[PDB]
Image (tube, rainbow over all chains, first blue to last red; front, side, top):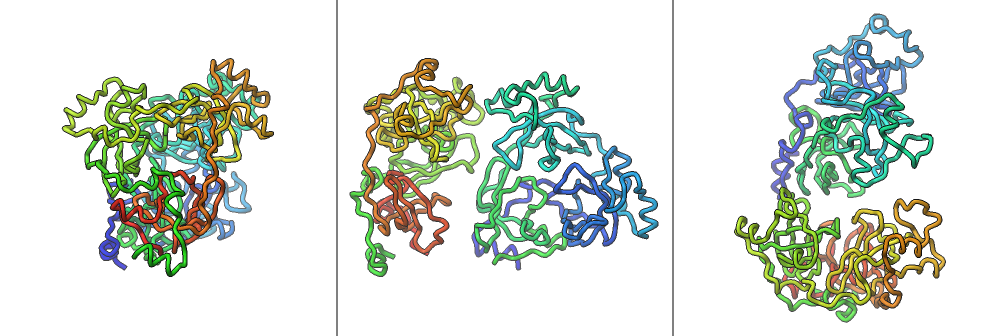
Length: 313
Length: 313
């Protein structure tokens, strides 16, 4: 419809652009991804692993990615400035494992041969914001240890490690567990803390799964034992609480069908999270989201990038 | 819209004024609180903690309070007869700790200097129902132990302590937790019981969060080692069940939007609680509330206090 008219009739305001990260707000970059182009990226459900991906669909500044060789039911949407995709050849050049297309073996796969065989184009390098050409985030090296909140069970703070570093971000892994609970973040993430934070703050520390003598867990001896060093305390940066207020309006991807982006409202707030409500729909669809999540955007984002906006119901 | 005409078309009745605590029913007191006045009060999210607060808005007999130095997102609403607010200087005079405005440390804070610097007025003493002038709740002293229901997880009766006493009320604290589960009450609360009650009643007692050997928890040993005594059994003076009956109508603060007060009905009853239904709204917004809660009121309270009432629908 139009935002201008909607804000008059609702007597409301939009969340100002300044409240968002530059990456959530930027509309002036062209989407250079094209149908059929090949690339590499993380599997969202297994964020430690990399796969060969094909551009299946483009919609404004977003794209839908397909896992080569696998079912179309695993297809997923990202923004064109996603740091979780990389150009062909990136795995080899940066020390990452490639999970190759269904039916191949890790070391049977060659990009050269694959491209000859498919007659496909690799998405050009200059499309990617993340190619490991930038010096890492300060003080977070692979193997280093920290304390991390299980985002799936937020009443737990757990023994964790850095297991991956790519440009300004790093992968938080929970020791002796699956990669299923892992997540990417930066040094200002409010979900991570230095070694010794639990004991100093009062809350208990969940030790690694199947660890000998769980209640008797000592950090300094775990470190010596695993030949690891703790991430240094000066590395953990303060991210201030966001400044979103209740009733501010914005645009948000619908989690029930991620092809769609809707008119939305801030229903509630925490220090680092906002509760999204889709205007005109039931509150039952309301969901909590991190303020720096890639799938929320300032009013106007859709119109300026060429993606349809679902009006309110 | 009137109450008389509504009761006619629904052939309904209002809960009589006599069912309510005097404090919930009183309409003839003026609200002397003014915009910008400063005061002290508990943080409702951390009820053991006291902060400098400013009057941000007034509406009838209710006011919205702002945490000096902090964001407006934390503002909250109380009644002008709230016992959870106190005049400037109260914390020093009564042995309470002040969490000072965002940039301060506790001991640098002085009211005289703050008033001089802000040019603000302290809310006058005469507005406050609770200034620690009244006689304390007989029997309940600071440091005494008892058994308390976890209102957030009501199947659990837990090891607890008295951590604060203010006039006829006291603060119940769950041993080894922070204060997020704590609550203020009086000797007639149905949520508290003497040391030994769980044992005599055949119910499971939850020991402190990380008591070394929980299965073998023993009150006589715990009391000895913490140098504490039990609140005397005689001090626990249960209130009788309330007499609100299903379908009775009243006014209640909207929990999702505390600025608003709505027409409401008793959907359901327990001995000490009532289930509130907002007339004309989904039953999914229905909620259980203590019968003595400050945010339910007899029909006519909004009109007599100068607060808008949201009619049904």
